[PDB]
Image (spheres, rainbow, N blue to C red):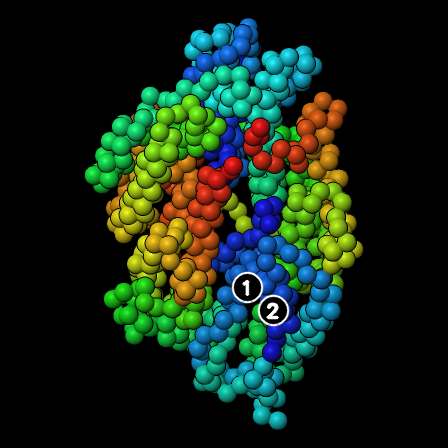
């Protein structure tokens, strides 16, 4: 799995748009969507929202958590904690990337939001490094990690699992 | 039974296949239903049109990726894929659709023939037969993986290594995420209690 | 000494990055198959003496020759199998028609393996959807409009 | 490139993978051995008893050959442990594993070491524990540089890594670079 596929799953996440056009509810294989009404909030998959925004047929609304004040508190929280803290969304990195790239005009303080989220990612990947060192040094064989995101797990998880596989062989070569 | 659920099942197989170190069970009923849905929708074919075709592409992509992943595994362990199917007890789920089986057979014949005509037949009388079941690596089930618990499971034994003294029990809670050896939770992947 | 020629086949492929395909080493393959013949002939002779006409003092030499045979055999098969894997890759990276640069470095037999392979893939992909459905060679990357 | 799925090494397990080019290269490396008999015709270091090798002859044989000629009874030959696995280096690895250049002293440190266990050396337990501890002690520095945690030249670190570590380095680097290209998709 590559990062493009992680984003592919993120695109399924629902977001709220403000249509500037009218249209009867559509019947997609994954579920009904709409109806659509000018000026009325609608729930649609991220990939559809992105496309409609590009097509300039709607306004993108930012997630309640995509706020400089809240993100600023989350970043400080993540730094104070030795473990991983609960992230706003299971696809916070993908939603920031896609929304800021296609609707920064609809997101206030987009510049700052980008820095705060980039910081959270930096602090969490670094923490993952320190966490893995502890896991390896104590030669652990199992771990719970409810707070990690898929993008994070996929980005450095092949390294950790490859290392664990080798250690397993080395730990059992005299058996 | 619904289309939405059909798609969820597919993505589940797609993800599980991507991370499992071995070839997983064939899901013919899923592939077919997805092919049908695409065919039907394709025929039904204004903005609503562009929206439908976009979704069709998303689904087509997952199917193709899933099927592509299965072929590489079939190719990687081809002798073991054929031997396992050969001794598969009646009733147990096959790791091969009728079509994938044909593909695997052909891969074997083609490679064995190529190997025979190019070098083996030109070797001494006592060194012309190479056991492919031994020459080709089997899947390594002692590979670590990450999973998402879909259904609560209890009394799961974690085996750090070959020293029974380090063994301990664990419980997997719904929604939680874990890191552990694949061999320990393989049956859970098959039953769908867990997701890789 | 022994099995050095076989090592040249391995180093050659090993220094070829990204899965590149250097010219098929016919000469190298021939020289190895010959060494095997020679090793087998020499060994088949000493074994006679060991049986009757010599001493069980040749056994150590006989094992040495045997190991050298198994070693040459391991290297050539490994060499040939790796080339097939790199060639298998070609179908998914270039398509069904290969460029001159690749086909000119491939052995006639490897070209045949490739064709048998693409013919089987065409059959698999065609049985997937209706009469002719789903080219899983396309949509290699997630859709993004 | 993407569709090329070569046979991976198996050196860390019971035995190497037959078709693994990397294991074939690893098993070509030599190890100290001492003859325990006479080897006729093989004297040309490849009249005197039909050109035989003197019993009790110290030789540098490729790992694969020694494996094939070896036997616990130690009748054909006996093997000595390369320096990098003896008391001396084991002590240095134990103090701090990061200082050693496993490329220069390897380059198949862990894989040769694992397969070396097949010779029933009395110090097999010392050799084995040394292999694991060395990887454990080097784990962090490899992960750190593979993800460029400190924005420093990795070429210098990668040059002192054994072949297994270099692969690990690759995986880590590939994962991060893939993420950074995605994150920058227009």
Contact, mark 1 vs mark 2 (Cβ under 8 Å): yes
Seen in the picture, residue A28 relative to B178 is either above or below; the reply is: above
**Nearer-the-camera pick, B3 or C119:** B3
Residue bearing mark 2:
C7
Residue bearing mark 1:
D24
**Nearer-the-camera pick, D171 or D117:** D171
Seen in the picture, residue B46 relative to C67 is either above or below; the reply is: above
Number of callouts: 2
Q: Quadrant of the N terminus of chain C?
A: bottom right
Residue A148: percent from left, percent from top: 34, 35
Residue B69 visible in the current orientation:
yes
Residue sitting at the far left: A80
Category of crowding for the residue at label 1, using alpha-carbon neighbours closer than 10 angstroms: few (below 14), some (14–19), many (at least 20): many
Residue D41: percent from left, percent from top: 61, 84
- The image quadrant that residue D86 belongs to is bottom left
What element does badge 2 sit on?
helix
**Nearer-the-camera pick, D4 or D158:** D158
Residue D137: percent from left, percent from top: 30, 58
Category of crowding for the residue at label 2, using alpha-carbon neighbours closer than 10 angstroms: few (below 14), some (14–19), many (at least 20): many
- The image quadrant that residue A145 belongs to is top left
Residue C77 visible in the current orientation:
no
Give the chain of mark 2.
C
Residue sitting at the far bottom: D47
Residue D120: percent from left, percent from top: 38, 67
Residues marked 1 and 2, same chain:
no
User: Residue B28: which disc?
Assistant: none
Give how far apart the Cα atoms at labels 1 and 2 are: 8 Å
Q: Residue at x 50, y 65 (%)?
A: D26
Q: Residue at x 64, y 51 (%)?
A: C85
């Amino acid at each position: 799995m590559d990062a493009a596929e992680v984003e592919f799953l993120a695109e399924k996440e629902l977001v709220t748009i403000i249509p500037n056009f009218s249209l009867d509810k559509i019947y997609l294989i994954g579920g009904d969507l709409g109806p659509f009404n000018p000026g009325l909030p609608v729930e649609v998959p991220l990939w559809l929202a992105i496309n409609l925004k590009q097509r300039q047929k709607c306004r993108l609304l930012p997630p309640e958590w995509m706020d400089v004040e809240k993100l600023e508190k989350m970043r400080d929280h993540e730094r104070k904690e030795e473990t991983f803290t609960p992230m706003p969304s299971p696809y916070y990195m993908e939603l920031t990337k896609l929304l800021l790239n296609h609707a920064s005009d609809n997101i206030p303080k987009a510049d700052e939001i980008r820095t705060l989220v980039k910081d959270m990612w930096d602090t969490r990947i670094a923490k993952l490094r320190v966490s893995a060192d502890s896991f390896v040094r104590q030669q652990e064989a199992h771990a719970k990690l409810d707070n990690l995101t898929l993008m994070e797990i996929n980005t450095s998880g092949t390294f950790l699992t490859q290392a664990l596989n080798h250690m397993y062989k080395l730990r059992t070569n005299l058996q | 039974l619904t289309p939405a659920e059909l798609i969820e099942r597919l993505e589940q197989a797609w993800m599980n296949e991507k991370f499992a170190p071995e070839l997983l069970e064939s899901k013919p009923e899923i592939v077919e239903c997805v092919m049908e849905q695409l065919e039907h929708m394709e025929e039904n074919l204004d903005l609503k049109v562009s929206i439908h075709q976009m979704e069709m592409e998303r689904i087509r992509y997952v199917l193709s990726s899933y099927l592509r992943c299965r072929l590489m595994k079939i190719e990687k362990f081809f002798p073991h894929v054929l031997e396992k199917e050969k001794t598969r007890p009646e009733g147990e789920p096959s790791s091969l659709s009728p079509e994938e089986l044909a593909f695997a057979r052909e891969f074997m014949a083609n490679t064995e023939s190529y190997l025979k005509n190019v070098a083996l037949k030109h070797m001494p009388p006592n060194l012309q037969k190479v056991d492919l079941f031994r020459a080709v690596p089997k899947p390594d089930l002692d590979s670590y993986v990450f999973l998402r618990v879909r259904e609560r499971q209890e009394n799961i034994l974690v085996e750090p290594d070959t020293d029974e003294q380090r063994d301990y029990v664990i419980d997997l809670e719904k929604g939680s995420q874990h890191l552990i050896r694949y061999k320990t939770i393989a049956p859970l992947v098959a039953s769908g209690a867990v997701q890789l | 000494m022994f099995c050095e020629k076989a090592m040249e086949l391995i180093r050659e492929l090993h220094r070829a990055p990204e899965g590149q395909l250097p010219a098929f080493n016919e000469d190298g393959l021939r020289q190895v198959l010959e060494e095997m013949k020679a090793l087998y002939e020499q060994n088949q002779s000493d074994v006679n003496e060991a049986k009757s006409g010599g001493r069980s003092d040749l056994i150590p030499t006989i094992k040495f020759r045997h190991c050298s045979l198994l070693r040459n055999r391991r290297c050539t098969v490994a060499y040939l199998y790796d080339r097939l894997l790199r060639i298998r890759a070609l179908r998914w990276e270039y398509g069904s028609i290969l460029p001159n640069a690749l086909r000119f470095h491939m052995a006639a037999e490897e070209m045949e393996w490739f064709n048998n392979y693409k013919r089987s893939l065409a059959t698999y992909m065609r049985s997937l959807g209706g009469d002719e459905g789903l080219d899983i060679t396309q949509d290699m990357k997630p859709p993004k409009s | 490139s993407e569709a090329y799925f070569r046979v991976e090494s198996g050196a860390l397990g019971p035995e190497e993978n037959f078709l693994s080019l990397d294991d074939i290269l690893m098993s070509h490396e030599k190890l100290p051995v001492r003859t325990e008999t006479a080897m006729p015709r093989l004297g040309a270091f490849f009249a005197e008893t039909d050109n035989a090798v003197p019993q009790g002859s110290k030789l540098e044989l490729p790992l694969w050959l020694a494996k094939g000629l070896f036997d616990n009874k130690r009748r054909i030959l006996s093997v000595e442990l390369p320096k990098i696995y003896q008391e001396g280096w084991r002590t240095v690895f134990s103090a701090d594993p990061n200082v050693v250049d496993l490329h220069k002293m390897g380059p198949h440190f862990y894989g040769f070491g694992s397969q070396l266990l097949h010779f029933d050396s009395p110090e097999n337990a010392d050799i084995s524990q040394s292999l694991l501890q060395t990887f454990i002690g080097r784990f962090r520095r490899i992960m750190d540089s593979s993800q460029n945690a400190y924005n420093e030249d990795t070429s210098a670190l990668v040059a002192r890594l054994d072949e297994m570590e270099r692969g690990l380095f690759q995986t880590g680097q590939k994962g991060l670079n893939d993420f950074q290209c995605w994150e920058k998709g227009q």
